[PDB]
Image 1 (tube, each protein chain N blue to C red):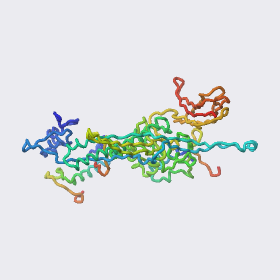
Image 2 (image 1 turned 90 degrees about the horizontal axis):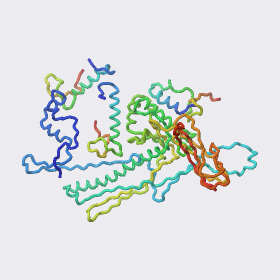
Image 3 (image 1 turned 120 degrees about the horizontal axis):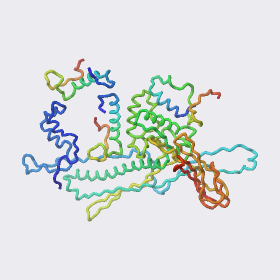
Image 4 (image 1 turned 90 degrees about the vertical axis):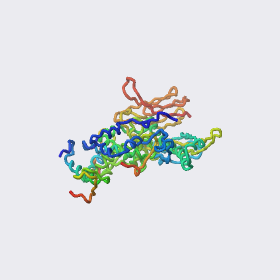
Length: 49
Length: 435
Length: 50
Length: 49
């Protein structure tokens, strides 16, 4: 919702972002979040924002 | 072996960045104007899919080569592995025995006079499990034809090993998936005690209500006096807080952290009780969360073998990784579902002494536990079938078997749902052997 | 003596979001139970001699 | 002067102040922070307010 517009948008940003970050590191892997639609998995220390 | 190899094969542009830069009016693309090879960088910024042969810019007839090959490897692992109970090397069926508690009797020495040796069996319930998964993974490696795609053994070899690694990853992924299947399965059969919840996420009020219901439930599950209300077997039992596992998912824990834990100061008063292990959600409609005992997961290994065979004629290897295992659920373990949306008025009628052996002409008491999802009253209609004249249930669970009975009996506990205009119902059931 | 459900209401909504929990806690002792039969009964406060 | 509507108008200057201060310390060192329009770079310990 574009943070700089209304407070709370930041909190929604944070939610979405943190949730996504979690998803990106789930042990079993996932086939989302990449342009090759391949199943993969990352690590938080290997993940940059 | 392809023609018309456009560089943007799978591209769905949102905008033409080249023209965006080209037409910068002092807007935010102006910082790329100082760049010189930006257009070329952009052209293949995301890499390419179909390799197109590229000739050397100086010689032209001389062709440019692949200078580096990077083989990437991912390790996938089953989160739920921690719930694996063990390994069964032989034999098939697994049996659980749960000795339940009993009904006290009113004191009366006048009856005791004659009933000293009256005997009474313990309320013991049992549950069986069978080996279920027996799948395998199949990969083919044409390791002679593959030689043409490499120029070194390091690359060739590591590639091959990657394929095998993929087999193991496959196993981990699917094992995980099967365990989720058990949850959705058990749910689909109406075997969880359903906590109806307002849909979480949609509001912080809903989220909060969810949390309250969660902690309250977790509390109930561990109370000393025990409870029958969390078991499909309706046995009274007790869980330990450290043995409770709440699954939920990443979406939910994010909201918990952001809306609740950052804004609270006394975190422990809102934290989820027991252990929490997020996953990728559940597929059952509305199944938002599952709270179960660590011993709910009846999971045992039965077989893990990789065998191979080469096809002379075809010059290739087949890899067969067999994975057998017992995947089940203990109905003696406490199990709770948090379900959004609408649920049935009653999800399950549990009739007790499932297996009886009434002496012909005798009788048997059947209790019943109606898993209501609400505070409404639900009268139970008892019914007996498969028997003959004089065999009937009086209601309130008392089965009266006729002296001439000889057929296996079915005892039912019907709970009506809705109006008589195509009324619905749930049937609990127990069976009786006639001695 | 309190139904776990009510206990949680306090816990989550009130004890959290407070700097001085001692101004919101329940007076007397608290014994959490599975609940009570009879519509509307949430918690019971009694003297030890009850 | 104008933070924008939606709460905000209590930290609007705080955010701009801190943001700007960070911009002057970006490693790549931008222009637009000095009257000579030169690429340059400041350090937090060298900034004064």
